[PDB]
Amino acid sequence: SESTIENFLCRSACVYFTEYENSGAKRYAEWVLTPRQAAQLRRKLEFFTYVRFDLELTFVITSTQQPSTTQNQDAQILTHQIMYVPPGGPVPDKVDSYVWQTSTNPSVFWTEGNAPPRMSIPFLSIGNAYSNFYDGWSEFSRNGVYGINTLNNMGTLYARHVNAGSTGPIKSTIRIYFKPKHVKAWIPRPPRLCQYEKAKNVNFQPSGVTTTRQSITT
Amino acid sequence: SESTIENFLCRSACVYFTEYENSGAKRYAEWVLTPRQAAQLRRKLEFFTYVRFDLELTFVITSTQQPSTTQNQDAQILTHQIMYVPPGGPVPDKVDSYVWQTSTNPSVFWTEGNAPPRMSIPFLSIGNAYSNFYDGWSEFSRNGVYGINTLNNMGTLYARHVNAGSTGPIKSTIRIYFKPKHVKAWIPRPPRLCQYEKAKNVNFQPSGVTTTRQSITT
Amino acid sequence: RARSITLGNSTITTQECANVVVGYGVWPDYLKTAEDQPTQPDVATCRFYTLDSVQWQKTSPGWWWKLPDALSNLGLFGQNMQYHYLGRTGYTVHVQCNASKFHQGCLLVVCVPEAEMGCATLDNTPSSAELLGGDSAKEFADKPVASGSNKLVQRVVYNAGMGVGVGNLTIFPHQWINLRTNNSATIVMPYTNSVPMDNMFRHNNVTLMVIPFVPLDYCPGSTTYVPITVTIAPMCAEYNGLRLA
Amino acid sequence: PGSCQFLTSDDFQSPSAMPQYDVTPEMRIPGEVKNLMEIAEVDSVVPVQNVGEKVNSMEAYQIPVRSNEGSGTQVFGFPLQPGYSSVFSRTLLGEILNYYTHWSGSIKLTFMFCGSAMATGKFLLAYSPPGAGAPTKRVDAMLGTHVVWDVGLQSSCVLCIPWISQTHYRYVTSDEYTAGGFITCWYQTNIVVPADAQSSCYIMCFVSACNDFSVRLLKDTPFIS
Amino acid sequence: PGSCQFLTSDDFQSPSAMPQYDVTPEMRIPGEVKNLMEIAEVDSVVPVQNVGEKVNSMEAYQIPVRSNEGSGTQVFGFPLQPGYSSVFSRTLLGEILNYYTHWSGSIKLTFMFCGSAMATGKFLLAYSPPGAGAPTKRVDAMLGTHVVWDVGLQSSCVLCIPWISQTHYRYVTSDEYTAGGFITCWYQTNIVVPADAQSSCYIMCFVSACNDFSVRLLKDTPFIS
């Protein structure tokens, strides 16, 4: 009963943690949607070849007062904007760009001190199932990289500070949770055995089959 | 299915961004309702001659602490007033005017830190449809300007600070979102092709028909 | 007693009992968008394509044949792949192995879908030359491939080049070959892919792996190898219509 | 989680700023648009000759045909991707298709020979399948899906190309698309005119859509600067 | 109390970021997984000889059998706990069982003698009850739950061990488990081969599951570093 894929692949897993400020060089966050960065969830997803699911994104945004020497401070409430760029959509080159205003990118404004913001993304493949494993080239020409189908593109995620609250410096961290929903899986395949190296490929270092013992009669 | 006008002309588009303060020369905002300022939405609206719709206005108000040297600050919560002046209604000449109190202008008071304020405006034309394009003069006399019917008047929008929160200076920015509802469109017409110049007229600079290529057999 | 199975021009000899292993309980049937996406089926393509035999010796790690790539050069299947663009096909492997009663060993014949191989160097991906072998099988390796600035596919036999445990490859449609009982293996593979039709030159649908778990052993005087032989038949293959609606 | 947040793409009920106000009833105005697909089904003149200063004039649309020096020479040619292609990105079809990220369907092409009532010739309109490259000669074109068009009998020839789909994400500009077909015209016979009749004549093309057309994932238009 | 809080393990309805978007319909792809138990019911080769450098090779799986020096000597032996045990923690069964904290059921074991068609012998597969220790000699093994396996007649022997359950919390590695049984093999008779036939032969083991298997309290996998 706990072994159904709905009960095996529907756990809120943290897949990204970063920090952006109201002043300074770092002013926004970005993260191409891809589920292969967290190994604990990648290893569970890699039990099947093709998986079709929906995503529930939960963001935990917390702001800390950066140490500074600016006198006479009195902060206001901070408002954040999380803009989710759908596949084939314009992406911001800077914080105060004109791409944050585009209407086809469903951004969500959230005011500090409430329930965490949350939005649900539907199946975004132009095909019939996401492919955990691909045995081909991205392009017909030699230029195409091996094992990278352009059909598992889930989009990108940009976050920023709508306004600078106080006159002092403030750093805000954003944690992203991944929760797959309505999961269907096809063609089960063996577990990893080896350790993971990169997020883009299945490259690995050859390892033993299992752990050793004193003797065969032990 | 995604090509129905209800799914093509019902996207929350940002159509105005300004800033007003609790002190100084700038003390309030104003913006005559008109949908021709944002080119991304204007170009979509200009696919049809007469369009009849309803408006859902969403305002995102964020206040930042302006740099200053005023000592001993301790701000209170800020309250804003957004007054929507209906067509043929009195308009304020200053912040502390007696027009902000009139009862026929449906103003909405919103206290900083909650869900953003939102109000819905119905079809305000005394005629049967707004005219994207007009091939006449505003007045019978020569004084009347060309292509400006006085039947697409959607009113004006004024915002201000109900009270000065602290003793220091504070600047508050207001973003306005336009969402048409119940959209009916008649007489489709060709896309712009040329770039936009002003918001009041269809004046343009002559441009080529398309982009070039090496040859006709290429 | 034996049997004969005539598909088109080709004829092949098989045992009365063949214990066929249908892939996922599904027979590779046809496809069940009108004028917008016309499709045309090809029949003569179906027939028995016999690949080159491989000699199985005592020091032999294993082999691997990509099912679409292997026939990319033989008959109509090789031709159709060059002419038509999109195509969906199913297969029927016929791995047969002949050795006397005085030989001993064991083989695993497994059809792996989307067998994405690894690379010696973690930074880059394997070259298509070291990945795709046409008109010839590709062999595994006993010791790990030395890593460096190269695009050599990882080919250790135990990791299988996909970085898993070689004892768990059974999850996929498979069949064992004990040189004292079973002498052949038949596996019918349906069309497994996310899309109804795919480009056949840019994507391998299925991969055929034959790995000997138990080493071949014989007494001095017997033939010092065992000629494994593979026969592939494309099944229910259809291609895009090149007409004009 | 998921409450007290403003999401741009949400459908909720809003409090009316001005209630108790009777909106004007609707009237019957001709030509009510229900779907954008109907617009994409009106034939639009295609600028085939968008070569150099031809675009900044009216001759971009007209295709020049000359009887002399055309025993088997090619008349014209272009790939078959509506949106993202110089010849079709600005038509009605292309302008509707530049709003969606995923579109598949069939395209209708109409050629109208605009010459004297006394001119006769033949043309060889060929359709190359997606993967196959554009034909090198008239024979290669004939050994395919051609249509021999005689302008003496018929003054207009119509085609219906299928397997038309999105070939790239975002926006790309490229001649000779890999996953798209090519339409080319060859001079089977030369233009035969009597005395006191111009032998130089022009053609025109009209691109439309079909009932089997889909459009998904609406995005921003790239023609706005 | 219990509202306006974010709990990772909660099932609520979320506002769709992108509504009015038609998801692609599903198709029939072969081999749809419904439950993880089906995976745990496929026989997997068991590395019985995981002794020294045997793991980093292919000989870890094969079990060596020698006719000489085996009048009654033990061939092999291992405890009967799938998960948490060097011989079974890496199979399919063990890998599924290393995700749950509580599991009980029955285990199926299949041995396949891989030798010449002309070799004959006998073996004595014995099952020790949980509390009882592994047998010291061939007699002790016989006075229990044994199965005399003749490789001349049958080339494969199958067992079905019950009373298999979780023996410890978290993850432990230990030889000779107290609450688990032991499977041992003894040479009843030696391998009898004719002339011109190898007498050194190997065996292989395959571990599976059964209909009566339960798995509860899913946790993290300990093989991730």
Image: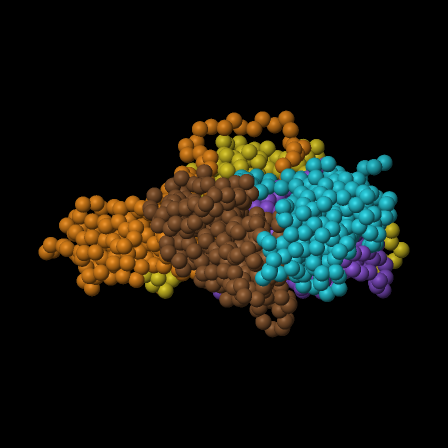
Chain colours: A purple, B yellow, C brown, D orange, E cyan
Depth check, front residue: D224 or C71:
C71
Instruction: Please give the name of the residue rendered at 71% of the width and 63% of the height, measured from the top-left corner.
Output: E54
The answer to which image quadrant residue E55 occupies is bottom right
Residue B40: give x, y in percent of width and height.
54, 49
Instruction: Please give the name of the residue rendered at 79% of the width and 54% of the height, measured from the top-left corner.
Output: A63
Instruction: Please give the name of the residue rendered at 40% of the width and 39% of the height, measured from the top-left corner.
Output: C34
Instruction: Kindly give the residue lying farthest to the bottom in the view shown.
Output: C149
Residue C55: give x, y in percent of width and height.
51, 63
Inspect this view and state whether residue A24 appears: yes
Q: Is residue C88 left or right of residue C102?
A: left
Instruction: Kindly give the residue lying farthest to the right in the view shown.
Output: B72
Q: Is residue D20 left or right of residue D83?
A: right
Residue C95: give x, y in percent of width and height.
50, 53
Is the N terminus of chain A in the top left, top right, bottom left or bottom right quadrant?
Answer: top right
Residue B46: give x, y in percent of width and height.
48, 44
Inspect this view and state whether residue B13 appears: no
Depth check, front residue: C23 or C13:
C13
Q: Is residue B182 left or right of residue B218?
A: right
Is the C terminus of chain A in the top left, top right, bottom left or bottom right quadrant?
Answer: bottom right
Depth check, front residue: D153 or C84:
C84
Instruction: Kindly give the residue lying farthest to the front in the view shown.
Output: E195
Depth check, front residue: A130 or B165:
A130
The answer to which image quadrant residue B180 occupies is top right
Instruction: Please give the name of the residue rendered at 58% of the width and 71% of the height, measured from the top-left corner.
Output: C150
Number of marks in the image?
0
